Length: 591
Ligand SMILES: [Zn+2]
Image (cartoon, rainbow, N blue to C red; front, side):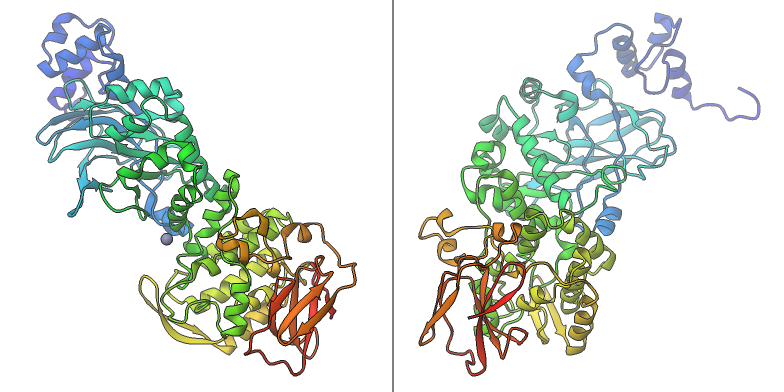
């Protein structure tokens, strides 16, 4: 009002004489009905509603909201070495049609820059919810947005969360601007009753459900088909699944304090299931196996499939080309374990003996001579043994969290140099355990030289030289000897499976995890009887494996088995070979 100041713009001057602030949610003291009626008609209707209490309560719950801040997704995908999470953390619950004019009244923004985004559909061969849409700049105060297209509105508020300007921003989308669809928020709305009511009153093709860690944005008519009246067990289940994967990654230091974005599940009208940057997807005809917990638990693969897909979002730090369809199964297997119904997936260690010692294979071509067709069933046991030993047997219950930390320090992309990355993984695993895991990684094929090109979502030079191998072994040798020969570990018993299940014959007779956990010792008088190439072990059930070694127990590994009866392959050289039993702690006993 001094001469030094520019006048306020015209509408701002008028609104701020009737209303407490530019959000127009409260009538200022001693304003008259005449002052209300001199407003533009659009704002008359709102002043009226705010003066009287005629704002439909349902409408108000979404038309007036304070939007909390969320972190930036590109920044955190880089720092955490993941695929990008969603930035659709902030639904408004308002839908629109092309040509709609939308008034958006933005309160104090504390210097933050925010926008509004309209999210609809994409696809050529079928349709799915898009990961982005029309973006509209927002400024503090009055905004009029004219919709280029239909969809639902999301507030885009992404910033540094620690800063004390990172506060919620109050935004009023008043009456007459678009359509209230609503959305369900777990913490705010709390109950299945509230969910059922919100869904009922919604009208849009899609309805948004916001959990703590994951969000659903699924076809309305499917939610009505499968879960008309309940969402809580569905949303808690998928929150837990995402949370359990996050647990292993050792990121509690930054989540939720600095990174808080959700994963965002859509329902494409095609494909099957997948995860990538910005969104994960479940074909809309499959949604019965997502939204009902009983369907999730009714078959092994109903939790496995989705867990696997989400694991792709999280694998990069510890993954490298050749492993891309197995390394995420650390997460799939952790989720099966957590849910408590089924046993772990993967081949048995016989597959690894066969690959390594019968066929001369290394990690990159383990069970795959083609170098482009990963034997995921064999590979997936590697990360999982590390979990079974350090976590399930409790020898180091923060092993994985530590290894993820170290691999994030290593900061190698999955594809830049996989031959080097496999060694960095072995070195960091040793560092994480504070143990020399040479024997483990030797068995798993990490110490064979490679010079070739593989294909796995791209062509990659795979190069592992003797010097790299020597450097890594020297590196790992600085740590104390491991307490157990847990390269022979299992978390499954033959009797847990039907006889035509692939695991029944695969898993072997010895090496079960309790033998490691109870530091079992071999006391009985083990003996071996050989006939041709066939080996039979008598009273050897206290062992965890049997080895064939050149010259003595410190010589090269020629073959191994976790069965008490096995054949030695034709290819193995027998002169100078000797046979041993392995007890859990790594003592070898001549047979
Ligand atoms: Zn996959």
